[PDB]
Amino acid sequence: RKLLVLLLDGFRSDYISEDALASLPGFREIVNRGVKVDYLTPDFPSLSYPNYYTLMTGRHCEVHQMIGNYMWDPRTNKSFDIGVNRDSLMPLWWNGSEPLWITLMKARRKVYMYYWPGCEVEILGVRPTYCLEYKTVPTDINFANAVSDALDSLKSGRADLAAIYHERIDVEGHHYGPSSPQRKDALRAVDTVLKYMIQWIQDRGLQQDLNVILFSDHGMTDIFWMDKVIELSNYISLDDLQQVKDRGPVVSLWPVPGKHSEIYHKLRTVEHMTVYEKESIPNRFYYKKGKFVSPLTLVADEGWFIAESREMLPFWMNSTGKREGWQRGWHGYDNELMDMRGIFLAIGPDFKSNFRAAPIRSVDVYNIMAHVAGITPLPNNGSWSRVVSMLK
Ligand SMILES: *[C@@H]1O[C@H](CO[C@H]2O[C@@H](C)[C@@H](O)[C@@H](O)[C@@H]2O)[C@@H](O[C@@H]2O[C@H](CO)[C@@H](O)[C@H](O)[C@H]2NC(C)=O)[C@H](O)[C@H]1NC(C)=O
Ligand SMILES: *[C@@H]1O[C@H](CO)[C@@H](O[C@@H]2O[C@H](CO)[C@@H](O)[C@H](O)[C@H]2NC(C)=O)[C@H](O)[C@H]1NC(C)=O
Ligand SMILES: *[C@@H]1O[C@H](CO)[C@@H](O[C@@H]2O[C@H](CO)[C@@H](O)[C@H](O)[C@H]2NC(C)=O)[C@H](O)[C@H]1NC(C)=O
Ligand SMILES: C[N+](C)(C)CCOP(=O)(O)O
Ligand SMILES: [Zn+2]
Ligand SMILES: [Zn+2]
Image 1 (spheres, rainbow, N blue to C red):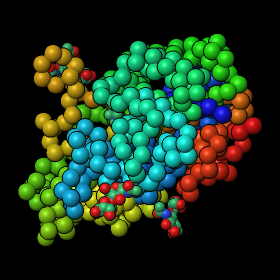
Image 2: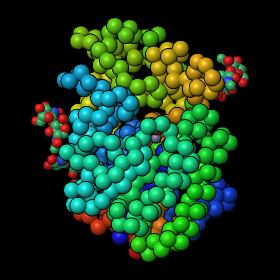
Image 3: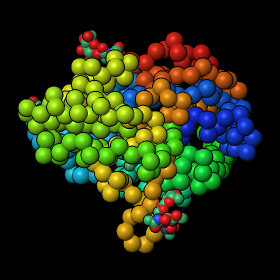
Image 4: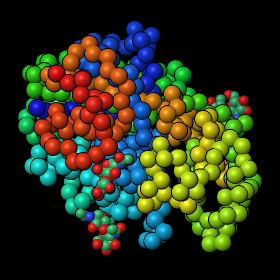
């Protein structure tokens, strides 16, 4: 039957703990009438673009190839800069595996996507039926309207799958911290939309024709500027680097020829991070085989933040003029950290009700989505055994 998928960026698993659900009527109703996993473990790195593609392919990042929010290809000398630069639209970055919406389009199913990062790309020669492109952070009004519009498109048969992306829980987790009232306010707004979404589904006659799946790409943890900042320019010269990508927990480095060993050994001494040669990256990350993975990768300890320098931190615009706001939450760290856990819930004719499911991994979600959408999944890294018991 029809499928509505909701991606809630940055939604940490314990945001809907038992204690939290006592004041979250929308999620409480989904929990009471559907499926909730204890938590969703993301892929490494626990960043957006990697986990977006893990969720929609069922494959680890070393397979689908989207291994960072920021990536560089030495062959073409082109960059993927968290989807902003025009070259992010190159199928080079996206053709490493076929995501579910492309498979559905090629099976002549109709797909509507709202603000979903990636829907604006021609992937493997294909695009979804409809894409409302992500431009800025969507507002809570944008979210409520997309949910209503998606239900209309599913009811009218213009869409078989509708997929909606919402960012603001991530933004407030970053700007104010995961335990902040600002983050809780953004969650409350989503909870209220979901409460009425349930009413809209019933009221428009879709309750028996529609499953709804909700998940997140990763959780969120506290960071501690300026004490817990690692300034790379205190240890190595940028002149010894061909390229550097990203700041924060996971940083990709490409040394100039002849400086690989020196950069490696110099950064090996730095406390509160780990530097890995590509061949020595922990196998459990299912990351090291990706073609875009850099010769050296830095992984910060939880709560620490790697940057070129303090003055080069990603300050945010909390005021009119220059960006001076400190970030208070972040993610990207070791994907087995409790704070990096995300969520998965489901409700509808094909899911059990009031069912607490064991924790699953980001790679497990694709098989579920494909099953209830009625399409054969492409071979992937999900475990059917880890998810099968939530289905009716
Ligand atoms: C915009 O932010 C600056 C920087 O201060 C950061 O301090 C943290 C509390 C963090 O939450 C982050 O949001 C915030 O941006 C604010 O200036 C700072 O104000 C504090 C007291 O609130 C002073 O102790 C600091 O000395 C001062 N630092 C600087 C560089 O000004 C600023 O108030 C804020 N602007 C607005 C309009 O709120
Ligand atoms: C997916 O995108 C890649 C990147 O554009 C395509 O491969 C490139 O294009 C041609 C294919 O032979 C070559 O000249 C390039 O060297 C390729 N670059 C690579 C492979 O990194 C690929 O063909 C696309 N696949 C589909 C099905 O459209
Ligand atoms: C994750 O799944 C992918 C896709 O099924 C696996 O990659 C395939 O592995 C077989 C066996 O070596 C190859 O014949 C295919 O060509 C591979 N496909 C791709 C797209 O790479 C991969 O081995 C799985 N990873 C793990 C850790 O189980
Ligand atoms: C990629 N994005 C800009 C749409 C969302 C935020 O990215 P991320 O901080 O969750 O990795
Ligand atoms: Zn995210
Ligand atoms: Zn984020």
